[PDB]
């Protein structure tokens, strides 16, 4: 006897079994019964303070002259204030650049995490290699102020012969695994699920904005991984090339039998 | 450099018969309208727009909690 | 005869790595001594 | 010579062929563009031999 939690949304019921015989196509028809009906003046034309259409004549000027001209993170407005007591004095010594800071001060928390996902750490390795009394604790001058990046006991701990400190830094995972909290059957589950509420606005621009925000294929690509065609064109080439999801940035689910769903199978 | 797609033009309206676009007529004016606008900005809007990314590419704000 | 899988096998004598023929022209043969 | 006539390739706005008003939808039985339900009634009860003459006047 299989089961699942209750579903609050509005799917599409199949008509009959004797019609769609072999070659059928599933459609993502999940919509919320809770709706929110907006006109095409507020949701599309000139009600949003971000959409730069006619009538909303401010949103182009305000976008340009607050994100690219009068901005204290554009590289021209950093290059004039980097020479002394001034405000971007410290930027030479943190392991960044002007383009690094300009990309870090405009993207999301998400896209900045994807940019962190393809940066090989090296200041932990300095403590492994450059570890002599004669070597006077060498740090690169363009990475000088990253002190806590440099002296880290974890980097030395991951190298030692006996793992007497690697059995202390992640003992939470060992205690969580040895209690059997991954093989234990999930006792509780939510009693109702629902898709997120969408706007019933009857323009094509609303459907374009919904399928570019609610789905937003850049985050889906950065979350699930690369296409196998991309893996073929990156692994049969003559030279090594990089990938924008360098690995599948989906986190490993901490429950082995039931991952990311609520569906229950009897046993 | 701000662009908006208004719709599909009504000369290409009945290409197919049940397409789903917003069929709007061709504008009966100029193609190059030149107008000037005087417009104000408060310095607090400069402070917020230089501190945190606002509005345009801040798509992770749809979570809501933190 | 796999297209993109590089085999490692470690037995009691030694341990050898086999590379398919279809990857020697690619960039994966620069370490193994084939290259482009 | 005399082969300088040229056709077109563009979406055509299809009008009614009973009246001259703009008509957005046709029929399965007789394939006539028609404006509303009065013209649909007069299409579905017209005497035989004329439903082909409307397509003959149209082409």
Image: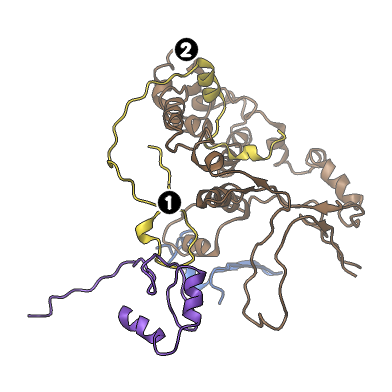
Residue A164's spot in the image, x, y percent?
Answer: 81, 40
List the residue tagged with mark 1.
Answer: B7
Subunit bearing disc 1: B
Compared to residue B9, the image places residue A233 above or below, namely below
Residue A152 is left or right of residue B18, and the answer is: right
Res. A69 image quadrant: top left
User: Residue beneath label 2, please?
Assistant: A86
Quarter of the figure with residue B63: top right
Q: Nearer the viewer, mark 2 or mark 1?
A: 1
Chain under numbered label 2: A
Residue situated in front as seen by the camera: A158 or A116: A116
Q: How crowded is mark 2: few (under 14 residues within 10 Å), some or many (20 or more)?
A: few
Q: What shade does chain B have?
A: yellow
The residue that appears at 53% across and 35% down in the rendered structure is A47
Name the quadrant of the C terminus of chain B.
Answer: top right
- Which color scheme does this rendered protein use? by chain
**Measured along the vertical axis of the image, is residue D32 above or below residue B25?**
below
- Whether labels 2 and 1 belong to a single chain: the reply is no
Residue A105 place in picture, x, y as percent: 52, 30
């Amino acid at each position: 006897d299989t089961s699942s939690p209750f579903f609050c949304g509005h799917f599409a019921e199949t008509g009959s079994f004797l019609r769609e015989g072999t070659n059928v196509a599933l459609g993502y028809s999940t919509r919320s019964l809770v709706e929110y009906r907006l006109p095409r003046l507020i949701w599309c034309d000139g009600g949003r303070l971000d959409k730069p259409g006619p009538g909303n004549l401010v949103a182009g000027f305000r976008s340009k002259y607050l994100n690219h001209m009068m901005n204290i993170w554009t590289p021209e407005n950093i290059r004039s204030s980097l020479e002394g007591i001034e405000n971007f004095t410290w930027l030479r010594f943190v392991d960044t650049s002007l383009q690094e800071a300009y990309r870090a001060s405009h993207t999301d928390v998400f896209a900045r995490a994807v940019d962190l996902a393809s940066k090989q750490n090296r200041l932990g390795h300095m403590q492994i290699v450059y570890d002599e009394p004669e070597d006077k604790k060498w740090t690169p001058v363009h990475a000088l102020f990253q002190i806590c990046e440099r002296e880290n006991p974890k980097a030395v701990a991951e190298i030692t012969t006996e793992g007497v400190l690697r059995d202390l830094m992640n003992i939470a995972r060992v205690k969580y695994r040895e209690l059997g909290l991954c093989r234990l059957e999930k006792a509780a589950r939510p009693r109702a699920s629902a898709p997120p509420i969408e706007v019933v606005c009857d323009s094509r621009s609303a459907v374009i904005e919904r399928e570019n925000i609610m789905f937003h294929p850049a985050m889906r690509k950065a979350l699930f991984g690369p296409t196998p065609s991309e893996i073929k064109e990156a692994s049969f080439g003559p030279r090594p090339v990089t990938l924008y999801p360098p690995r599948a940035l989906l986190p490993a689910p901490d429950h082995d039998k039931q991952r990311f769903t609520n569906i229950t199978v009897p046993s | 450099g701000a662009c908006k797609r208004v719709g599909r033009s009504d000369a290409y309206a009945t290409e197919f018969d049940l397409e789903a676009e917003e069929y709007v007529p061709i504008p009966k004016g100029e193609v190059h309208k030149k107008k000037e606008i005087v417009q104000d900005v408060t310095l607090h809007d400069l402070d917020v727009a230089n501190a945190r990314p606002q509005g345009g590419q801040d798509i992770i704000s749809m979570m809501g909690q933190l | 005869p796999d297209p993109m899988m590089i085999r490692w096998v470690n037995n009691k004598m030694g341990s050898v790595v086999a590379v398919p023929e279809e990857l020697l022209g690619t960039h994966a043969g620069v370490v193994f001594g084939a290259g482009p | 010579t005399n082969i300088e006539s040229a056709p077109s390739l563009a979406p055509m706005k299809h009008y009614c062929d009973v009246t001259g008003l703009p008509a957005p939808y046709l029929d399965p039985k007789t394939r006539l563009r028609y404006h509303n339900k009065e013209i649909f009634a007069m299409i579905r009860n017209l005497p035989q031999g004329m439903g082909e003459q409307f397509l003959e006047a149209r082409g």
